[PDB]
Image (cartoon, rainbow, N blue to C red; front, side):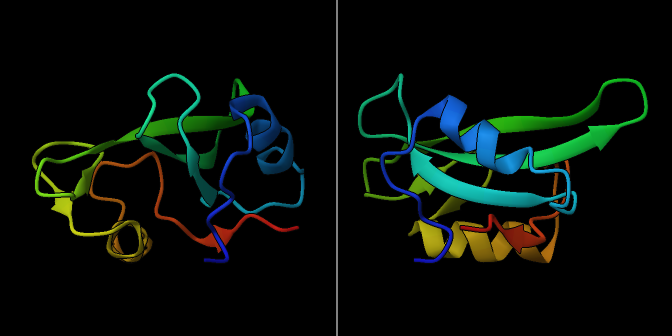
Length: 102
């Protein structure tokens, strides 16, 4: 619930995620703006050339009702997806480390 930001836009999610004191891996889950029914996991990242940046991963819907970023790793809920990537990056730009503040 804490990390579910609902109908926040892609750019508003970037504004919040790009706060300079957010550790790398700060994230939120939102409804996708461009794919109705899908969600997005937006994560803060960083590299030493470009600096702070946000990576967006579309979370698409399954026919069983599940969710997935890559079809190779499907979940029965967004809570299960968030718990999984908080445990290990498994291909994400970085492990989910902190829920995006306020």
